[PDB]
Length: 130
Image (cartoon, rainbow, N blue to C red; front, side, top):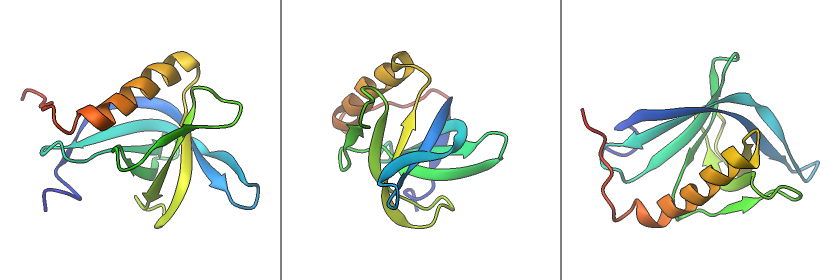
């Protein structure tokens, strides 16, 4: 009720999704897809989910909040992981899952903006015209 739904799609981007392998202790790709952003009309929670493009299937529904923190992968500077409990149909575990963009360009722009939005989006209204 205005929380687990109520989200609309504003932006989509081709990204790689990663899972943290407990057994590998390491981030390994979940696949390749498009990061779909669903944003609540309330602008309370926004999500980034990514569906595997050619795989037609969302694997991770991650909410972008300051309640969570982004951390760069080892060796990556601008590809980051977040801890989220994903269960788009990903099955509810909390994992640190990662996503990386092709370049630190895509990765860096998003990283900065991501954190800023975490602190900021909360207080600052961002409503898309209709």
